[PDB]
Image (cartoon, rainbow over all chains, first blue to last red; front, side, top):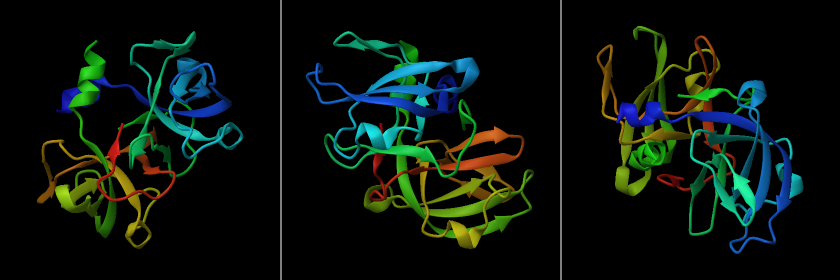
Length: 108
Length: 110
């Protein structure tokens, strides 16, 4: 199962913009995330409306799989899969590092 | 695509550190962890290379994130049954992942 894990590119990023996605059928927040200079500035549509509001996400470090294939949600290109614990259906508790790390830090 | 299927093979969960001990005997210094992953998975052991930033007394009751279906690895006489995840910002350095809010032990990551 090591090689399954090593194929993934799991990285830290900081949210720099967040917006409710009212055009979407399933409630979501559009995220712009700084993954540092090399991975770059990336987008994500995240179903995190239960616990979070846009203003409270700005400047938050998050953990994402950055080598997933992208997917367009009602016009919006979602490039990165932001990870969370799922305590219940439609519930997400975002993962974070327990203290600040540089954007684009590799998870292992 | 293959990357999706590889991720879907992983069983990533939250658990609480209930025991912690310094592990200087390991090839790279480590801390031995005993983690409660809830009723189904139960109690699991892990060795983590986290001596730079953490001390055992400060790890007790901490929620961590681990791949629980990682096969066991054996380090200096000690059976590490799960892979505890952290950011690796530098040589020898680890920053532990955590949920940003408390969740039940065994909560699945996705």
